[PDB]
Amino acid sequence: SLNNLQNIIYNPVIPFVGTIPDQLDPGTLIVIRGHVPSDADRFQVDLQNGSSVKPRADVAFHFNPRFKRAGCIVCNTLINEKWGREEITYDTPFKREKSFEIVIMVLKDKFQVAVNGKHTLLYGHRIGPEKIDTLGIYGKVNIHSIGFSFS
Ligand SMILES: CC(=O)N[C@H]1[C@H]([C@H](O)[C@H](O)CO)O[C@@](O[C@H]2[C@@H](O)[C@@H](CO)O[C@@H](O[C@H]3[C@H](O)[C@@H](O)[C@H](O)O[C@@H]3CO)[C@@H]2O)(C(=O)O)C[C@@H]1O
Ligand SMILES: [Cl-]
Image (cartoon, rainbow, N blue to C red; front, side, top):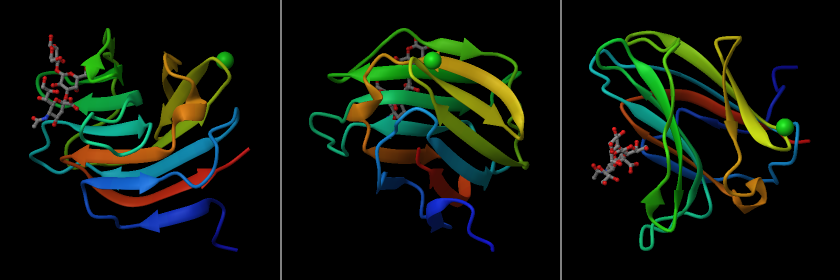
């Protein structure tokens, strides 16, 4: 059959703020397929505790490809409206005008992210993943599909 992921969302409007339909237990996958527009400066995928804007929802995991200069991916955590220490990954596979697949795997102590079938980065948990119930996608990105595999 054609359904290999759960709770699939197709061609969402960006910015996208959606409820994650089950718990992010170890082994859970979040799978996002899309493409970067030619003028992209950045986009972000945020795993959030709720969707409030005041106070702004905590972001357990901010995954933020940036396209200026040589490009990079910045990761961070937002707690009580304050950003923490950035973790920057310089070996970035994202490119303007190219399509991508992001697979975020939740593990016990960290997230692991693979892009286009290749391991890209790790990010240690700073907020318990049990607090995450919302997926936010913002910025200059086109999203084809979002799906989940819940453990
Ligand atoms: C309306 C708007 O522009 N919202 C932005 C916000 C605001 O600009 C910002 O929160 C106001 O302080 O920024 C968002 O991106 C931030 C996020 O990617 C973090 C991750 O660490 O980096 C912030 O920039 C850093 C920069 O990377 C550092 O080099 C610098 O020393 O500090 C900067 C500020 O901390 C980004 O602004 C956000 O999600 O908060 C994107 C929104 O669209
Ligand atoms: Cl782990």
